[PDB]
Length: 433
Ligand SMILES: Cc1cc2nc3c(=O)[nH]c(=O)nc-3n(C[C@H](O)[C@H](O)[C@H](O)COP(=O)(O)OP(=O)(O)OC[C@H]3O[C@@H](n4cnc5c(N)ncnc54)[C@H](O)[C@@H]3O)c2cc1C
Image (cartoon, rainbow, N blue to C red; front, side, top):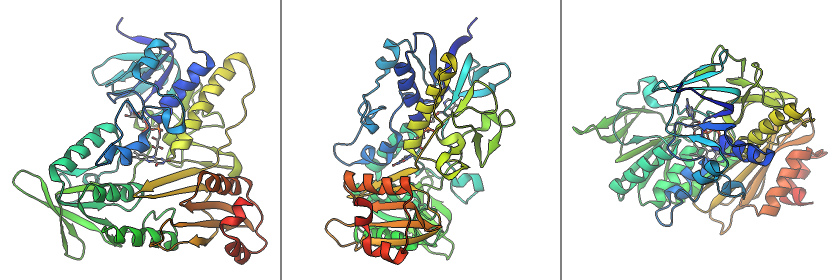
């Protein structure tokens, strides 16, 4: 009798959930039809803000300001946006069991929820140094950043330790955005990572060299090809230092770690087909279980333009896959045709006064173009990835919305390159024309 049933259940209260709810309201959802179950205590928000505006030392972004869908220029969805529509937000509720055969979800406290259609939007986990048993990685003030709860703990630690020393472990987008956030919050910052350069799975050595030099000039000590092998801590269990493989010690009042993550799909293992580490879906985000969909970070879906199954961690995909799934679900109900998902990979990052965008596929060979001098007033440079005589990928730092739209069009249309050398001479003009 305490069990709750909903025609549609979104599991997770993140970017994809929030955008899926907007498409349900667009599609004409009736009160009582939809529930969003989330372990977070707040309504869906624009997660990229957590490593950006949330950490500003002045005029920081705070909720309710960055709830979905403001991040894409849409309208804000306060908790009241859901309740007025009879869309039930079930917050601070962690689902610990999902039985797809009985369409039942069970919470940690044993509350049960059944559905007709399930949308899996559980996002990604955070890989922790304690997962590998790294010596003293359990020390207090060794922090990770995924959710607003993490962001609040980081904000509190920054206030407690400001004027102090911070070490950032990891050289990916988290490493880069957090090193900058700590520096702008008046910390002595050291960035350490074992790979030969930052954003190792996306940046080329030449792109990374710009960021390493720019960070160095901001006063960030960048230690590439360096491995953190332990941590020192005091009688309170608070971190005091980061030990390096060579034997060096970095003093630290705070340590922030960003070493990637994995699709949070533990609830569904063995119940749905998996591919390339994610839950496999078709062009409509439907899994191997009929009526079960998977969106955002967890989906391994058909990337139409590359004729392959892919998995991404992009806020743009999170928003668009959410809209696709809802359109597909409502399409099956009415028997109306829905086009296959046609996504152009798009990733971006911002730190200090920098901002870059990437579109397409980072395959083939690379060429660098523009002004890549880190001391430039307004640096503006890019890179193209060329394979089989055509541009597959495009990167641009410091572009205007027009220049970013131009490099997106290059990645979308994959124009031929008769002369790669000649493309390097054309640079940013190649995209704009
Ligand atoms: C700090 C940060 C900065 C980022 N910056 C950028 C950026 O600049 N550009 C970019 O393109 N991408 C960025 N990303 C990536 C982007 O935010 C993600 O791709 C996006 O959030 C994916 O949305 P999602 O809905 O799939 O997952 P999430 O937004 O993570 O949503 C998952 C939700 O499900 C909940 N959940 C999970 N398991 C359960 C459970 N068992 N029970 C209940 N609730 C559960 C979670 O608590 C959360 O509410 C960033 C990510 C982070 C963490």
